[PDB]
Image: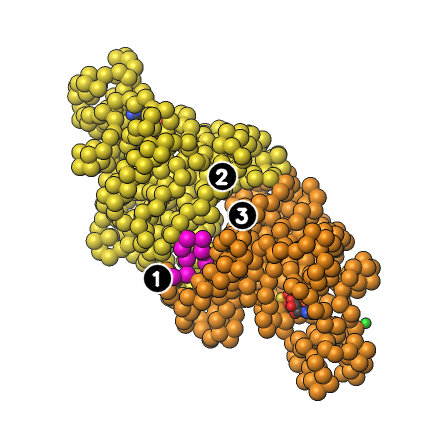
Chain colours: A yellow, B orange
Amino acid sequence: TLLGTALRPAATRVMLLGSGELGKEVAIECQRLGVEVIAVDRYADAPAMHVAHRSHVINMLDGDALRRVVELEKPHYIVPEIEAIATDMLIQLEEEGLNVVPCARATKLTMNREGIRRLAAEELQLPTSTYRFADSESLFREAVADIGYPCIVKPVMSSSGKGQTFIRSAEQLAQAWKYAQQGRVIVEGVVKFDFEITLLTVSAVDGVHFCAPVGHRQEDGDYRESWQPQQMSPLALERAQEIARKVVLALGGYGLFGVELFVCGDEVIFSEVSPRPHDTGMVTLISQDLSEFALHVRAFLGLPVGGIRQYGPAASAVILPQLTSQNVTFDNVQNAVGADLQIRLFGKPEIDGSRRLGVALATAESVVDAIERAKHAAGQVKVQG
Amino acid sequence: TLLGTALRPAATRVMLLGSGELGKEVAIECQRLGVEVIAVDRYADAPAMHVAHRSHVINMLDGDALRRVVELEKPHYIVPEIEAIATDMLIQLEEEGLNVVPCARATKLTMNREGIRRLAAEELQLPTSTYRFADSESLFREAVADIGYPCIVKPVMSSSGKGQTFIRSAEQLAQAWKYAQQGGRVIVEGVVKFDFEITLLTVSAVDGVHFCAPVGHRQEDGDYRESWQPQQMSPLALERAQEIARKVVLALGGYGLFGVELFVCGDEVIFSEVSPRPHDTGMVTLISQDLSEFALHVRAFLGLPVGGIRQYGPAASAVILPQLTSQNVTFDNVQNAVGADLQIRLFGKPEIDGSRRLGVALATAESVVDAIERAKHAAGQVKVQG
Ligand SMILES: Nc1ncnc2c1ncn2[C@@H]1O[C@H](COP(=O)(O)OP(=O)(O)OP(O)(O)=S)[C@@H](O)[C@H]1O
Ligand SMILES: Nc1ncnc2c1ncn2[C@@H]1O[C@H](COP(=O)(O)OP(=O)(O)OP(O)(O)=S)[C@@H](O)[C@H]1O
Ligand SMILES: [Cl-]
Ligand SMILES: [Mg+2]
Ligand SMILES: [Mg+2]
Ligand SMILES: [Mg+2]
Ligand SMILES: [Mg+2]
Ligand code: NA
């Protein structure tokens, strides 16, 4: 591995496609190794751009645009932060010699539930929830019919629980199908798990390594809190890793992956996977020697991970206000930091509704205490408009 | 404590005067809190400018120049990273309402050896080496004869051991003086024979004075080569060291992290000098603590409470200090400089012309001895070319 000096002619260049808070930390980790960072997004002043060398505002769903910025910047690595990109142009660019992290196929399979679900379920023969894909309400209707209640319906091209609907009644169908169209879907058979985890799996030169399992709390399709390590059976864990390894290897390429699983007893079920750092993984900003962000960069740059140290019970708790403003201020911060307590404020230029503006990070003697400590600090911050 | 959003009208603005690798980290820590950062230095593309919202290049020794840029960016805080700045204007600005970190007086006192030495030694009555100042070659010679041999002569305005001579005899008098003139006034200090020296990273915050675990370091030709933490010391030495550090920081005044340099002779501690800001030897904290010295400085000067500092066990830093002339430096064999319990930092410095710290290797282990070896080893693996 040979790295140049940022801004100099031999500099190594990283293009970030998506400049939110996750991209912001990858940017910091690149900066730490003197890697040149170009932050791209669909709006100006996205958090990653504050810390990048330069930025571009584009319609990332626009392949030609994507091609134009890439071509212009000639990056060594292209790192997408989100799903909402023209993965087709990624494939081409890759085919053309660009290094897409972890690999372009990976991005593609994961932006569509059909791909990923089929791969895992069918191709890899892994435990997942019961499901069915539908192209028409009739079929939708037909499908929900076969899955039963309750059931989840999601757009094959959805995230943050967008267009999704939890179905316990035939009456929602009308709207359910409509939401899911707001035109193909999946109907999944609700799983009754003890808890949900994120298994942060890094694929690198020295193989696949796992971070301690990350548990978390979702609400209204937003993770609220995450913690590490989530208490799991040795057997349960062994199984989770097996599934994660098969999947990551199956998708291919070096990088940090967020493998979403459900745990019931010693039983593990595959849900989905992010071919990049996952929001729940923000707890690794205080819980490990190497954050998920640092791991992603180490991996993609072709460097060996070797090992991941975990520092005890730890937690993250989001700062998720809901208001409209283009001039947010945060008061009472002195009560949101302290021993074994930190906070991050993203630099997002405005908000109009519900948005994640920062996160509180905490460590403690117990996972439970870590969670309270983190929750309490996020809650002391007064978000003003 | 109220913080705005960077780039927004109510943004909280921080101006860094000096954009080196130390400033770089301070900038990342500000950015992590959505703090707006303007990086200033005497050359372009300096490390911290890589991560700043905006950058300017001026003569920071020029009071007028300084005032212009402050007028132009209207920062809430002015954060000096080096000694060579218009301290007299800082004072003005601080009176004109600007927050100089930790304070403008602390900055004036420490910009020259005389200010800080007389304060510590005379006003604070802290233990220090014997010393004598001199402004002529003859007075220089008079000071040596009074101080005796061996002794060390140093220019009053300097750092990273520039123009310093470890004088063992009269033979060296002449060259010593000349070289000293190369880096006016000089200091002649008596040689302290300590067991080891430390940097005690002291944080003055709204909630008091906090101490990081002692950092030991090894110096060579003006540059620190390795640093490690914690450095073992008796309980008594640790207490005396913390008493000294608390006195000096409070005496200097203001919130921030300070780098208190001490010599340790068994249970006795002697004051050497102090950085009114993060210290290069403290880079080990980038791997060894929950909050690096940079995260700490920011926390403190923003007026937030520290609460406390977590130390993760034995660790060390080892500099990447090549010697070459280039404006396009590259680093190879990187795959053999990082791994389990092993990391590196590459600063992004635009050029080199001789010896210059371009990065640092960091490692943790079960003992400082193993950490240091691991870290020197990794730094050594890096193939610097240009
Ligand atoms: N079959 C299922 N059984 C039980 N809970 C489910 C099921 N599918 C989803 N969930 C829950 O819903 C959350 C979001 O479901 P996802 O399928 O991950 O949706 P998404 O829109 O892709 O959200 P992201 O991308 O993970 S943020 C999960 O984290 C679970 O809490
Ligand atoms: N009186 C003294 N006795 C014995 N050793 C000394 C004495 N003064 C300095 N040294 C040694 O020389 C090193 C450099 O001295 P400094 O006074 O710190 O020089 P410097 O130019 O200010 O370097 P910086 O500011 O730390 S980068 C110290 O870290 C000690 O190792
Ligand atoms: Cl004197
Ligand atoms: Mg998803
Ligand atoms: Mg999910
Ligand atoms: Mg000095
Ligand atoms: Mg010194
Ligand atoms: Na001040």
Is A331 located above or below residue B27 in the figure? above
**x and y, in percent, of residue B385 in the image:** 41, 71
Give left or right: position of A351 versus B301.
Answer: left
Q: Is residue A114 visible?
A: no
- For disc 3, the neighbor class at 10 Å (few under 14, some 14 to 19, many from 20) is some
Disc 2: which residue:
A312
Q: Point out which mark residue B119 bears.
A: none
Disc 1: which residue:
A1
Which chain letter goes with mark 2?
A: A
- In depth, the one of A206 and A353 nearer the eye is A206
Which chain letter goes with mark 1?
A: A
Query: Which-is-in-front pick, marks 2 and 1?
Result: 2
In terms of image quadrants, where is residue A22? top left
Q: Amino acid at mark 2?
A: Gly
Q: Is mark 3 within 8 Å of ligand 2?
A: no
- In depth, the one of B279 and B115 nearer the eye is B279
Is B296 located above or below residue A363 in the figure? below
In magenta, the rendered stretch is B336-346
**x and y, in percent, of residue B71 in the image:** 64, 54
Cα distance between the residues tagged 2 and 3: 11 Å
Disc 3: which residue:
B312
In terms of image quadrants, where is residue A280? top left
Which chain letter goes with mark 3?
A: B
